[PDB]
Length: 59
Image (cartoon, rainbow, N blue to C red; front, side, top):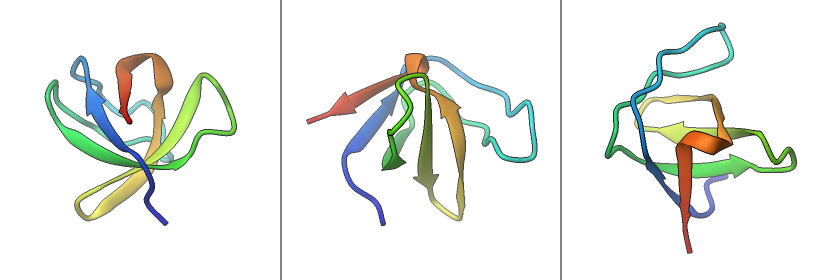
């Protein structure tokens, strides 16, 4: 389930079936940050992976 809010810092185009597409300024929720570089997130009707470097954890 969703935890911390996340801010998208730059547009990102999904590069695999496991990723999602987001736009700069989008607000997401965090699902899995076990890996420092790749985070699972939830955004509206979709869940998937994004590069952690593109995201600011809002805590």
